[PDB]
Length: 625
Ligand SMILES: [Ca+2]
Image 1 (cartoon, rainbow, N blue to C red):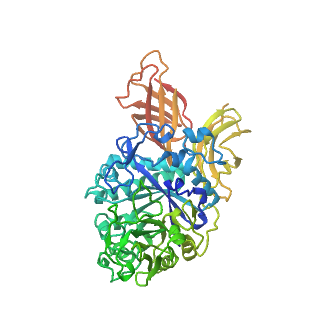
Image 2 (image 1 turned 30 degrees about the horizontal axis):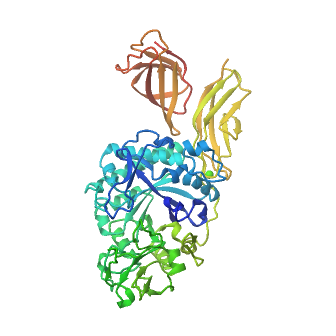
Image 3 (image 1 turned 45 degrees about the horizontal axis):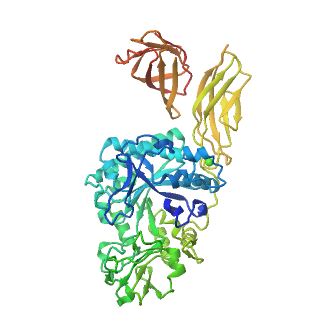
């Protein structure tokens, strides 16, 4: 079974004019969204003004229009890369109010992804973090137990809030300096493993609460050097899979012409012995102990170009000279006065304007199995991938036993765009035909999330009114079924009124959420007695047990010293913090202080916490004495 994981660039929605709606998600199993960032000292971004940093800008993390970030944000927090594009921008006919986008971050690209998953109900969404520009703080965050925890907890909250199915870590690169000013340490090797364990544990906890199986992945470096600075074998066992970046092996940072993503060893390549080609890199990974089913092969939807390059061997493996601007790289598709020359071409741009056009001639290396363009007149050389080379790579994926293909990125395929119109065959259709056999046409298999925070809104001798937090689904939640002994009820909203009940009777109500395809959540329950200050709240809940909280308010004309809470609860409580359980009889409970919780002022509140087993009930007949 094969995977197709596509990268969506946040910034594609501006000049490149590639919107979420444009995406045909029948051709994907997974969509990675690039990028989110790490908060540090109240800002995020990379402030380095070194020339290898393409985005020398930082932003404050505190954002009044984003509920999760409407506060002083602590160090290590996962934060939105660009709030306007990510959650603030309003999209026409989406159903969003002004308040939803303006103060609740329910709009933007994340809103569009929610609509996309509904349209294509097999699709799983991942938030990618870091990347080349925003990897400056991973080392700092991973070096301390406290910032690893903050990061892992923020990741779980991010996923829940904005509807992602997992997180992808793109740390470029542990223990090595990429952009001067960025943090990196040798202990990054042990600390990268600790971070992934800390994230995985957090995701497992939350997946049990939520009824989801959350995914964890990384994007890793295709070199022995990356292997030498990480514990690949260990991390392969923690992750769902590894997106190996088997591209950018060579480009306009070097003075010899070469291939961006060569598949096999070409001995005629001066750099053959560095293993900077696909099969070399896979051999590096397998030799480290990485199972080949844990690798998803990266492929590029772009090419790389040098501006002035020697004429022998049709431009291949020749010396290159810089231009008037001092750079070796040619003027790529999206390059302008502010970017300078980056040598990066969308495949679309190449196919519409460069392949056997404008003086560029296509040649084929039948050893490396990749194409390249050379213009004898200008001296410009371009390494790229096409449908022919893509078909060789899909054959490799199937023969070597890799588990899929990842590609960078969605907007670079043959499309019509503000700067080119390509009408020829699409790289992505090659990946689909070759790895899946054809577009995916599957039904919803993803169940809705578990019901939470069941409360009794009102109670009667013969009736009860229940409310709960609405569950979520990828397509939508159609109804809730409530059971108690022999009886059954249902509702299309997250509340119900139940009538015709025996007075002074104990009932245990189990609630599950359904979707249209017929999936369902796992039951959650609450115990209620019909009729004839301490407020009890449930902080976290898996099936078997839950964490709780009690706030004790003093409405007194005196201070409360050595307080003792007495109440009855038709349920079992196991552990209490900031408190001790004095006694129990027929679900009646006596609780006492921890000695430094003795004093509660009149109008003051003492807050204590505990855990329980089974399902929650209602704290009743409470007294403070
Ligand atoms: Ca579903």
